Image (tube, rainbow, N blue to C red; front, side, top):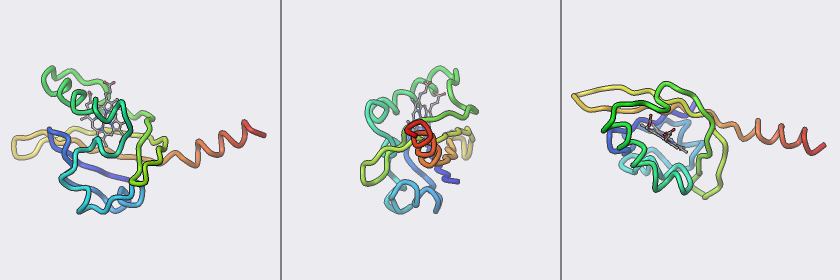
Length: 116
Ligand code: HEM
């Protein structure tokens, strides 16, 4: 599914091909951008504080957990997505992998079934 890797400051390091299809950005456009560009406010401005919180305290909240959130595409449309975060280390620095699954079709079917 969509895979994204960031360093300890939330900057995107690797951006899969599927992530390019899901979010709109090419990998070259994405690499070097903060991860907060893939999500709407209030989370967007808050995100770096979430990572900071985790880094200074070492007490996890969603690391190793899989949850549903709203992502935000290049065109600005929002969508529900299942997010799973992995923490890794390399060259002495922490990295984080996010595996995303688009749930837009699940939300649509569900709404349609409720609508009818
Ligand atoms: C694009 C949709 C995303 C949203 C809405 C989002 C939102 C959030 C929120 C709300 C928190 C704090 C959760 C809590 O304190 O309970 C958080 C933490 C964090 N997010 Fe994201 N995130 C997004 C994607 C990502 C991705 C793609 C990555 C990794 C590649 C990532 C990495 C992190 C990290 C490292 C933390 C700290 C975890 C912790 O506090 O245990 N986020 N995110």
